[PDB]
Image (cartoon, grey):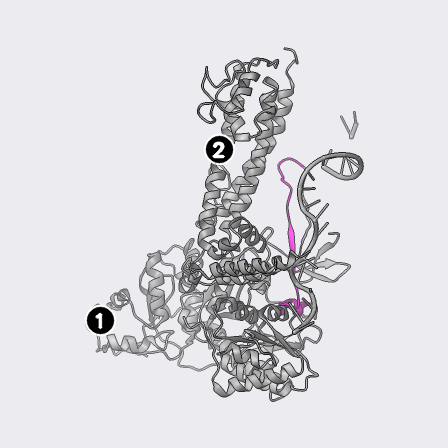
RNA sequence: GACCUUUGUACCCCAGAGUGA
């Protein structure tokens, strides 16, 4: 029935958009459910961001099944326009993937976002 | 192609030799595929009358995709799951392990699968239509008293559920549905319990509260080649 | 006859085994299909014709 | 205390009387004795479900702390003890939540659940087979298996879009049927190639040729008129029938008896059966292709849809995956990947999302030209 | 007493899991 769970609140959404902004600054970001599915195959994916205003929505339902197979966190965001904007990118991106790097300059922000997401998934 | 296959020390798990150390089991489903695994066909047929030629395929078992094959390749002393027993399985994430546990429990043995996330459950209903030994029972794990009629008494319980609070979950299942002197095997993901602290104190209090519920641990181990920051613990009930 | 007909046995016994191959082929196909509705039958009755 | 608890299973609803438990405490004599004996408990009464529809509906009720009415009827047994509520009976069960329900419909009855994992309740289920007093056991654990199928299958599945393998069986059985058509077709064209060596060089069709050998059996009577066989399937004014008049005169083949021909009538009837089931099954594949994957048959039609899902094995398995022609084929790959994920999820693929998707394929189809 | 390989014919003319303004 809901099909839009979990959907994030306000300050977590802008927090995620800022983390995606520095992630696009550090080329540690994947753009597209095609690419995101490939990163879920290679096991390099930290977590997955999906949009809620994508028409249709059922093209994006494969990512929770593949993530729950791989035990990977995921949270919906309401805008695909702002989700495109946080990529340093001027046309919308429906879904983005966070890649794995322990040498990442922004790693603590990624662990805090995974703390909020993994808090919300339970 | 050209490999040879021997019976290992554990009953029900078969070793494959030898241009890679490979771990295989017998498939009771002819020519099925669960995740694009590759199958090795080796037979002891007969060209004589009265006996038709056998067709036997074996399935490899990725230790990256399951925790138990990673457990066996890492070295582990005994396995409580053998031909003949009953086994209660927790965690149902993709059903990939459930095929191999269904292989190792034999056609005598019964596999009991538990999940609450309703969308992967239909896959296991389909595999239940494929393999006639995988019995799904779909419910929240936290209330096993809600399906008191729905399962028998079990020799051994395996838990692969990542929670912050799995200790009460195996407490209720262990107090309810387990036989005397059975086996309890628990999987642990490190950061699921806590992440603000070392994993090792989490291991100590994990074995501690595990020991408060009348469970004797035998040996734990760390899986450094295969799945980093992850450990499995093997113990007895009322030993 | 003009040919001294004996070749038709050689044809027919070449056809009979392929007929049984189609027989257990389509019988197992029917078992694969009908197993959805009623799987518990093949362990009890195993013959194709009675199936 | 005043104890008289209830054993619950798929196996019959049973009321058992107790003598006394151990008010003695948790040591390693009483637990290890009561693990395996387990006398001090006797079977008073019981009642079967014996409805495969009945048991599951009851199982949701006990699974949600809700009583059934046969449970009230089996809790109508205290009469030779001269009363209820002089008893102040204490029940002990497995559920917390069922307690306040029984206390609601019974003020006569004290009802607790302490202890929740009271080991006497383990003492029933660790020795249950021996208390099958008049009860079967053979299909009883089979009712355990299938009733577990009934619960887990019941709560999430309603046979919604079942054709994840039926389409694959249809295309595989169909293709092996066509290979089996060419099998008998070569044998019939060899056979009538003996008796009449020219019609095999005339009609290239298989089923047409099979009916021709089927209903004639004589190379001096096969014409459009006297008798009429090219006035029913084909018309006599065709360019074939004049060559049939041409061929029925100048034949020099072997003249064979009827006994050799009746076996060939069996062969032509086999060809007729094969053509029958392949046309009907082809129609069925059109129907369920229109049903279970509508947007895919909007895009690429029936055949490549059935073949590609026949590669992946299910629409879920196709769903989880990902010289100036491969731009078009790549575009079709992406949009068919999208349409598959549409068709996977519940009856919004009944709409025309794939139709405007094919309109986008028409737009890209305009785009490669310019 | 004790099915395997070669010649000729038809078809296919070979981006998917590639890369990522």
- Does residue B78 appear in the picture of this structure? no
Q: Secondary structure at mark 2?
A: helix
**Both labels 2 and 1 in a single chain:** yes
Q: Determine contact: label 2, label 1, CB under 8 Å.
A: no
- The circle on residue D57 is none
Residue B61 is situated, as x and y percent measured from the top left of the image, at 65, 62
Residue C12 is situated, as x and y percent measured from the top left of the image, at 60, 25
Q: CA distance from mark 2 to mark 1?
A: 74 Å
The quadrant of the picture occupied by the N terminus of chain D is bottom left
- Residue at (61, 81) in percent of width and height: A88
Is disc 1 surrounded by few (<14), some (14 to 19) or many (20+) residues within 10 Å? few
Residue marked by disc 2:
D273
Which region of the structure is painted magenta? Answer: B48-72
Question: Mark 1, chain letter?
Answer: D
C23 and D174: which one is in front? D174
Q: Is residue B218 left or right of residue C29?
A: right
The quadrant of the picture occupied by the C terminus of chain D is bottom right
Q: Secondary structure at mark 1?
A: helix
B175 and D221: which one is in front? D221
């Amino acid at each position: 029935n809901p099909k839009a769970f979990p959907l994030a609140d306000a300050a977590l959404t802008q927090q995620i958009l800022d983390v995606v902004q520095q992630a696009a600054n550090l080329r540690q970001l994947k753009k597209g459910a095609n690419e995101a599915t490939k990163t879920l195959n290679r096991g390099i994916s930290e977590f997955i961001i999906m949009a809620a205003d994508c028409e249709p929505i059922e093209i994006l339902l494969h990512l929770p099944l593949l993530c729950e197979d791989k035990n990977v966190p995921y949270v919906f965001v309401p805008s695909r326009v702002a989700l495109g904007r946080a990529c340093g990118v001027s046309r919308p991106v429906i879904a983005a993937s966070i890649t794995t790097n322990d040498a990442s300059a922004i790693k603590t922000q990624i662990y805090a976002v995974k703390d909020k997401i993994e808090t919300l998934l339970i | 192609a050209k490999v040879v296959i021997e019976p290992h020390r554990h009953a029900g798990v078969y070793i494959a030799r030898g241009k890679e150390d490979l771990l295989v089991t017998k498939n009771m489903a002819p020519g099925e595929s669960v995740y694009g695994e590759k199958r090795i066909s080796v037979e002891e047929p007969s060209k004589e009358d009265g006996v038709p030629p056998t067709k036997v395929e074996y399935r490899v078992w990725n230790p990256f995709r399951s925790k138990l094959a990673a457990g066996i390749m890492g070295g582990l002393d005994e396995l409580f799951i053998a031909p003949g027993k009953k086994v209660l399985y927790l965690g149902a994430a993709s059903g990939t392990s459930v095929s191999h546990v269904s292989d190792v429990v034999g056609p005598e043995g019964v596999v009991y699968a538990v999940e609450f996330s309703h969308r992967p459950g239909r896959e296991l209903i389909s595999m239940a239509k494929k393999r006639p030994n995988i019995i799904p029972i779909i419910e929240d794990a936290r209330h096993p008293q809600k399906y008191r009629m729905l399962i028998g008494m079990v020799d051994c319980v395996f838990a692969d559920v990542a929670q912050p609070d799995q200790a009460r979950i195996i407490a209720l299942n262990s107090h309810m549905f387990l036989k005397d002197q059975g086996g309890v095997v628990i999987s642990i993901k490190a950061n699921c319990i806590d992440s603000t602290v070392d994993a090792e104190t989490v291991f100590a209090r994990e074995v501690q509260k595990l020991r408060e519920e009348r469970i004797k641990p035998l040996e734990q181990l760390t899986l450094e080649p295969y799945e980093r920051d992850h450990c499995i613990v093997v113990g007895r009930y009322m030993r | 006859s003009a040919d001294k007909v004996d070749v038709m046995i050689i044809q027919a016994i070449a056809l009979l085994d392929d007929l049984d191959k189609e027989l257990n082929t389509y019988a197992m196909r029917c078992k694969e299909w009908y197993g959805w509705h009623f799987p518990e039958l093949a362990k009890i009755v195993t013959d194709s014709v009675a199936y | 205390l005043f104890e008289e608890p209830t054993g619950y299973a798929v196996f019959k609803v049973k009321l058992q009387q107790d003598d006394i438990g151990s008010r003695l405490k948790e040591v390693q004599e009483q637990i290890n004795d009561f693990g395996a004996f387990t006398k001090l408990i006797e079977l008073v009464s019981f009642a079967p479900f014996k409805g495969a529809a009945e048991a599951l509906e009851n199982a949701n009720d006990i699974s949600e702390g809700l009583v059934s009415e046969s449970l009230k009827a089996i809790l109508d047994l205290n009469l030779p003890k001269a009363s209820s509520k002089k008893k102040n009976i204490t029940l002990a069960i497995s559920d917390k939540n069922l307690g306040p329900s029984i206390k609601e419909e019974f003020p006569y009855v004290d009802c607790i659940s302490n202890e929740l994992a009271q080991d006497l309740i383990r003492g029933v289920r660790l020795h249950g087979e021996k208390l099958f007093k008049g009860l079967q056991s053979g299909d009883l654990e089979r009712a355990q298996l299938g009733l577990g199928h009934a619960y887990s299958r019941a709560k999430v599945k309603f046979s919604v879009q079942k054709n994840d393998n039926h389409i694959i069986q249809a295309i595989a059985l169909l293709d092996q049927l066509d290979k089996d058509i060419n099998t008998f077709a070569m044998r019939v064209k060899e056979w009538y190639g003996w008796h009449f060596p020219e019609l095999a060089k005339l009609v290239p069709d298989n089923y047409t040729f099979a009916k021709l050998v089927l209903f004639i059996k004589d190379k001096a009577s096969l014409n459009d008129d006297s008798l009429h066989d090219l006035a029913a399937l084909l018309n006599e004014d065709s360019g074939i029938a004049q060559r049939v008049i041409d061929n029925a005169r100048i034949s020099m083949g072997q003249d064979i008896s009827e006994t050799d021909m009746e076996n060939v009538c069996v062969f032509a009837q086999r060809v007729a059966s094969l053509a029958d089931y392949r046309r009907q099954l082809y129609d069925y594949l059109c129907e369920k292709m229109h049903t279970v994957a509508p947007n895919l048959s909007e895009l690429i039609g029936e055949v490549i849809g059935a073949r590609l899902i026949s590669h992946a094995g299910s629409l879920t398995n196709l769903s989880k995956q990902a010289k100036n022609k491969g731009r078009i084929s790549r575009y079709l790959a992406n949009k068919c990947s999208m349409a598959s994920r549409i068709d996977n999820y519940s009856e919004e693929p009944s709409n025309v999302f794939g139709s405007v998707l094919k309109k986008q394929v028409e737009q890209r189809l305009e785009f490669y030209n310019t």
